[PDB]
């Protein structure tokens, strides 16, 4: 199972 | 928290119009001019055969990777979108999981040439025969027919910008915690979009736009054909498919 969306949304 | 979560004035609606058209321009992946400046660089019969000769798993990998890259710009558009970042993380994920593919399918009509029925794929323009090795002919003709329909509307970048914000900001997505907060943002973007169509004398395309069931059917067909490929090549998905793609279309 993966969770890359949480990272993309946080990464600024 | 955010202005667009309450009733906005005509002035505020005007700033939302420029905000959305701005956020879109910064995240469009390819400029419209670059895409129109290639309509003549078509794949040769030899190159088309080359794609057709590729295995099913290789064709799926190439396509999943291209889908993932296009989705990544859609995530950026979402982040730069007015009000999206003021929503909770649950709702941000809900909206992106349901809306990302639908945005890519809309954005895609720019990369499609209605004159020769070709799409800009890997550097050149090729017809739907290029994707014959995928083994999902109904899905490919459905995605081409949809882009052919949107191409007939003669969208401006601003219109694509405004409409793609609406496709994403959908208060009817199952699993939304702050449903009323998404309802107000959707209303303000509907106002923003309809204001521009009014101001540009383009309100006639409103009746010519596709139903929300059409974007759903295409997304569901994609998940269906992915489940079929996954059953045939489980390791290819597990080992060679991008994690963002798996997260959006296989739930991990
Ligand atoms: N994963 C997946 C399934 S269909 C697809 N497309 C087909 C149209 C061109 C880009 C890639 N990707």
Image: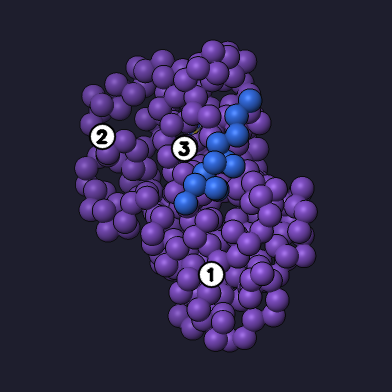
Chain colours: A blue, B purple
- Residue B209 at x, y percent in the picture: 57, 62
Q: Residue at x 66, y 50 (%)?
A: B89
Give the class, few, some or many, for how many residues have Cα within 10 Å of label 2's Cα (few <14, many ≥20).
some
Label 1, on which residue?
A: B205
Q: Residue at x 49, y 60 (%)?
A: B80
Secondary element at tag 2: loop
Q: Residue at x 69, y 80 (%)?
A: B7
Is B219 left, or right, of B180 in this rendering? Answer: left
Label 2, on which residue?
A: B43
Residue B67: image tag: 3
Q: Label 3 lies in what chain?
A: B
Q: Label 2 lies in what chain?
A: B
Residue B233: image tag: none
Q: Measure the alpha-carbon separation of dots 1 and 3.
A: 28 Å
Give the class, few, some or many, for how many residues have Cα within 10 Å of label 3's Cα (few <14, many ≥20).
some
- The yes-or-no answer for disc 2 within 8 Å of ligand 1 is no
Position of the C terminus of chain B, as image quadrant, is: top right
- The yes-or-no answer for disc 3 within 8 Å of ligand 1 is yes
Q: Label 1 lies in what chain?
A: B
Disc nearest the viewer among 1 and 3: 3
Asked whether disc 2 touches disc 3, contact meaning CB atoms under 8 Å apart, the reply is: no
> Can you tell which quarter of the image residue B49 is in?
top left
> Between disc 2 and disc 3, whose residue precedes?
2
Along the line of sight, the residue nearer the viewer: B143 or B29: B29
> Between disc 2 and disc 1, whose residue precedes?
2
> Between disc 1 and disc 3, whose residue precedes?
3
């Amino acid at each position: 199972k993966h969770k890359i969306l949480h990272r993309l949304l946080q990464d600024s | 928290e955010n202005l667009y979560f309450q009733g906005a004035s005509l002035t505020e609606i005007e700033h939302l119009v420029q905000s959305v058209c701005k956020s879109y321009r910064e995240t469009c992946q390819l400029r419209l001019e670059d895409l129109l400046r290639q309509r003549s660089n078509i794949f040769s019969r030899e190159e088309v055969t080359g794609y057709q000769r590729k295995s099913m798993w290789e064709m799926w990998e190439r396509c999943a990777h291209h889908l993932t890259e296009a989705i990544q710009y859609v995530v950026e558009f979402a982040k730069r979108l007015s009000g999206f970042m003021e929503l909770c993380q649950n709702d941000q994920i809900v909206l992106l999981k349901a809306g990302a593919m639908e945005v890519v399918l809309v954005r895609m009509c720019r990369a499609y040439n209605a004159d020769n029925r070709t799409v800009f794929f890997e550097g050149k323009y090729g017809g739907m025969e290029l994707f014959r090795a995928l083994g999902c002919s109904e899905l490919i003709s459905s995605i081409f027919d949809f882009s052919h329909s949107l191409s007939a509307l003669h969208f401006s970048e601003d219109e694509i910008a405004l409409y793609t914000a609406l496709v994403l900001i959908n208060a009817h997505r199952p699993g939304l915690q702050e449903k009323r907060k998404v309802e107000q943002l959707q209303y303000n973007l509907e106002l923003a979009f309809h204001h521009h169509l009014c101001k540009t004398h383009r309100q006639s395309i409103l009746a010519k736009l596709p139903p929300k069931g059409k974007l759903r059917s295409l997304c569901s067909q994609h998940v269906e054909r992915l489940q079929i490929f996954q059953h045939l090549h489980p390791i290819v998905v597990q080992a060679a498919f991008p994690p963002l793609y798996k997260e959006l279309f296989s739930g991990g």
